[PDB]
Image 1 (cartoon, each protein chain N blue to C red):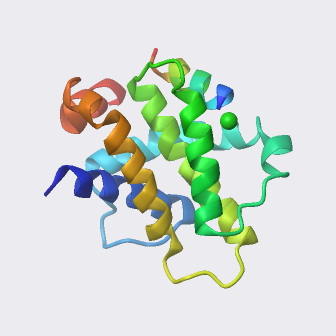
Image 2: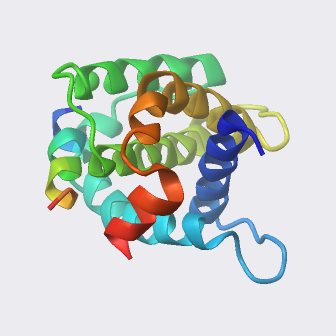
Length: 147
Length: 13
Ligand SMILES: [Cl-]
């Protein structure tokens, strides 16, 4: 029940929904369900907008996947602006990375989605954690604006 | 990153 652990659970839950890994009987939390619907509302459109760009990147490893994630995330927020919509795109992008990694990584570890979700949660809490605290948090700011 | 940024602002409406 820590701050990083809750963000890690959200990041890992979404990758399970993207890869369509079945969870316990009932689905994840209501917060992860609101997040999954909003990020699904985005993901397929982002892929179909960046097919030329994504078809030319080599996401062949975890470090390689982390390098590209850090690179895109630093330029997206290079204006110093954070909102709940931009946070949704952080989850939407990790879903595209894990699908490119699944198709390009040779001999992956079991549950590689847990490794990708880990450094994705590190970025969210280190660079948007203080902002999330100051705009209602997850149960009062995010859910209450998309539900 | 430009794409994702405006996809995000879009939903912030
Ligand atoms: Cl970029």
